[PDB]
Length: 212
Length: 10
Length: 220
Image (cartoon, rainbow over all chains, first blue to last red; front, side):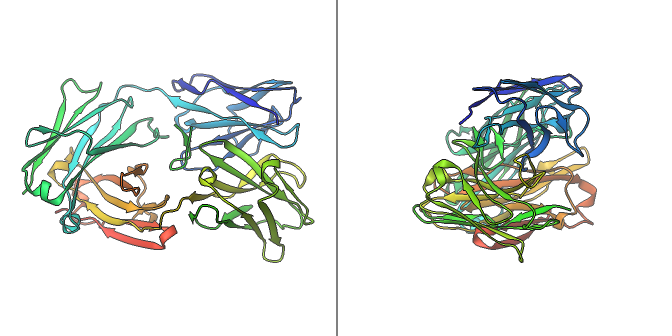
């Protein structure tokens, strides 16, 4: 099978820059390469066929070039809606094979997170478990620290984090940290605090509530 | 690696 | 409009078999071949096989012995079946159609079926409100959400107000808990002055367990 090698694995650029994806084939394939876009939670979208031929409905800023073994997909002016993974496909040799893909990340200005905290619902407490959720909304860049404290006891190992993919409209990230306690432990304590560190904040932000 | 939850590379 | 609509996601026990239906519209199966592609964490996008206009099938070499593709032209249905599944067969499976009847440049894709291979059992989620309050309000904006806890397997669909509310929605990727069950939250920001007039409902659909919950989220 043809091995397709896409490089690099991640591309980070600023809006309006030109950007180029590379696809190298393990032996000559002429111009028998197609390019695909995959957005968050999407199916692959066909961008270019046969190295450089355009596709109806695809913005003009997409173009491809190359022949033999070395191929290039180009975006002349990146928009935030271009945040996606990009894959190349060869079909000069059965079976058709795909590259492993390149991720296109976008830069933007530092944006501090908005921080919200949610106590557990009385509904969940009936079931015997308590989830406390801390939300970090629409921030950049992705790096942040979330630290939980219960009655000034530092929590460690009983929280999980999830981060959305990059927003295709405004290039921010959002993060949830969920602290999970038993109902008994939760009822045994009063002050629940989420403390947040991020480049866009000049001092840490603590959001907190007293149970009750 | 490709992530089944988001369909994106992680 | 060319479309390909695949059956829904679900769990398949190891060693058991996989079955997906792809229903097409906007073209006839007697004129185009229908291809099957999958996307795994292990191998990324792999081409699996194709059933051609006239019934012939090709299968990618590693799959010829456990893969079968059939179709019903009258019903516009293509059937994908794969035997003896193991855990690294956990993937999103897609049906696709090329630009021309004989080619392989896939301009039309199904939405993809996420198949999980695992010995576990199907569990529907519990849905708990993440209620707006002072502790989630800032400069006229209130955040609120739904906690979608303890289900298996992926995925779950979450929407807000039956699709009419999409702006400012963030549905976080599921995380796997030590229990082996997934959990996620979905949040949205709204004007805090709308909390007394507008109702906010997260529509939760966990198709592998046929669990549909509409959770009304209220200021506490």
